[PDB]
Image (cartoon, rainbow, N blue to C red; front, side, top):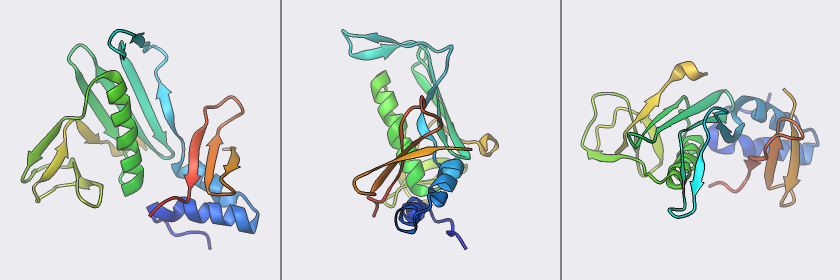
Length: 187
């Protein structure tokens, strides 16, 4: 029958199937649908690394592909502002994308704009104790600014197996960058 879609264990179930059943079908399906990762940099955007400040300089545009859902990140260096557009609504994929964008911003020399409010009338990206969720928060929490949920943003791969079958790395072709396809080290 396959696997029902539930975010924190889809990849774990795929890896189990591929490991003990022997067919790498569900891993391929996961890679096709919701597993691309990586950092797609714009060809026209060139960054210069400054050794004095240990930070990159120059306009940068990164698209974070996560399968059917993609995250578009635009950074305005002149105004020291960023625009984050994504279609990810699930929990831990959103957490991973937030971590990646935070690391990119740290490398670029800025941080996320966080505002503590007791309620937002519109849909904003807010962080709770259970993680990151999209909606209207009526509870005093932390809301990340410059976050827009764009629903309009919505194959063969090879997999290398490590840790005796606990983590998986996939890529489009032989020259494609390596990204962590799946791993069972969840909670």
